[PDB]
Length: 183
Length: 184
Image (cartoon, rainbow over all chains, first blue to last red; front, side, top):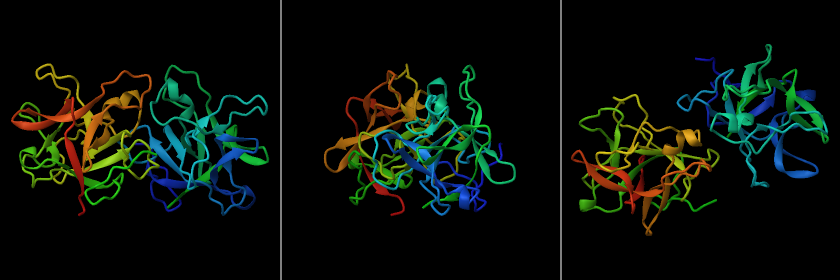
């Protein structure tokens, strides 16, 4: 089977367990990903990266395409969902999805209100993959295979400034991350 | 957000943990639920009820629709997986699902080889709910909400004799169970 993604402990990523997604480049490279919100719009929440490298952000849970496989594997479609530690401020889901195109910035954002499950055309924008990033950790990729007939975007996920925050978006060069177990 | 399901100790049912599912009616109401098999079918395994009220049967684990919620709640879709004490003879799953209609009996049986997670049309038959049956008991119900566009069966789960054994099937009124922590 496909090679497993590993956390910083070298342990295989397990679907359903909570992990921080932390920049593999610390210092000026910032910290972990978090359930963010635009200054002018509080819902749906967006995916942002904390600017301080010790702020790991909000943990995520992975949901495997292959339900019988407990391991999150490279180059394999999955759903990702934030697990907020605070009470919800929105009723939208915390599941990552690619947004509709943003004409005001030229970006295809990673935002929330995605859908867990039902791989196919209805849920195309909610399926992500992890690939190796050079020799420095791991990289998110949006290139779903869940709908063989669908035309889809295929691109790495990078970071991009917006609203005085660091958001995630489709980009030529993917930003590298490591995975740390979260209690 | 809904009301939690409680075990016999008054404690909220924890997703992920092993619980016996024991009939709230003892004596001729029998005991707990268990993996079974038929004469005409070794695999997949079926859902049966042990007939002795001292037999708690096979422990189960509840998988919430929402993995972020550590609590099994009422009127909320979940998956149920038997955690066998003995080793698996069948390699099919121990996850409950509603079978295809059985023309020989008129029954929609609760069997196994269901699927954990992947909420939506592909797993519709694997989602179950718990409803109140009085004040000390809980009834199983099949009426999934995971696929808004799907037409679905919607019915309580009761018991029905088949093959000399007690099976579970869709029925107009549901059988009441209590939940007992298996570690205890």
